[PDB]
Length: 128
Length: 78
Length: 229
Image (tube, rainbow over all chains, first blue to last red; front, side):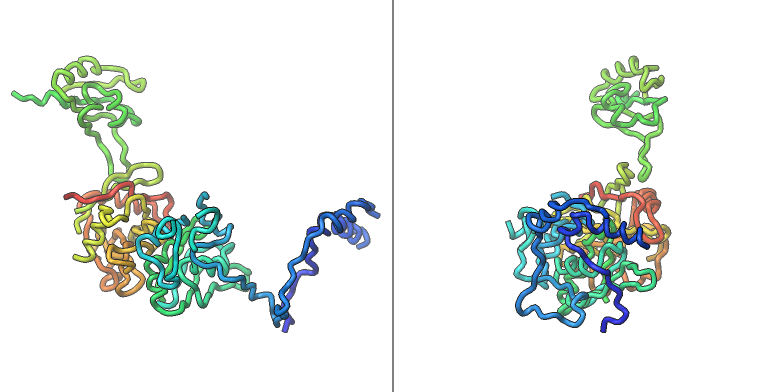
């Protein structure tokens, strides 16, 4: 099924990218088409600066595509992501919960509480 | 009313900040935010199908309160 | 025979001098009592002269003898004996006042001008402005298009008419538009409910900030609003 889908070659981790071996390998490939940077820094990146990868659950079987369905819980009413805060541009209620004052609590999520109205808020999350 | 048309957006927005964005109001059951293939970029207008109609009429009332990239967002029935 | 020796006439004013500059430092008793000056609806820029009133007559006469041929702003000025509204601000500049004549649709808009139901138009914007068409606002805590709420719940013959924005039949909230031409293609689709009685010039200053796609070139804010009652 993945005939025309063109993906990247390899996504290396931060522990390998912070060692300088990728740039030296790219320079060697450009020269062919050696470095001797360090010997203890690679051991430090392999032992001390080791990053645990994102594993999966025991029932998390591999689907067919498994790349276009990046689903994640259910970010609901009162809880938003950072960047979209940036587009919104409000310094640390999100301002359409000013209009959730006038027009009323949403039919879709009736149980709703959002800060300052019936919900008496810190960081991102302005409603529960 | 179950669906709405949404104009005036910036392509850094995608189907996800619409998902997240309009479910802040009430859950978007079916999302449609075209990806244009030819130049690989978005024109920025949207169609939203909800659970039923009440969700979407409240959505007409409240809904035109989203500002995407400092800029205005059109929401009307459909 | 008259006792109108309170209102003093100031001439040779600068382009920066206004009711404020004259108040804190005018000819006679200007800054005091009341002050009159040539103010526009969109431009809102004084010419060079004006009229200042003094709490008393003696104070006024003394202000003339002095302010007479005085030096203000490096210039020599002369002194001698002489329904709802929205105040609009465009960019950082007051533009002037639009007065409007407005049952259920009129009452909703009236309450949104007074804020007597706990919310309304004050501080909101005209978010969609299209030259030779209309200026749309009432997305108070929205600044989008058809955003807001009515006092009841969630839900065209020429220029200077008030009409309800909507998202189809029976979807009136708080969003409205002021027409900038005959917009008869909207007849039977939007509910017309009032008319501009004063400040059509201020509406033209709002329209001047429009674009074909409706994006305002500068922010247009309802700085204040209320009712004559």
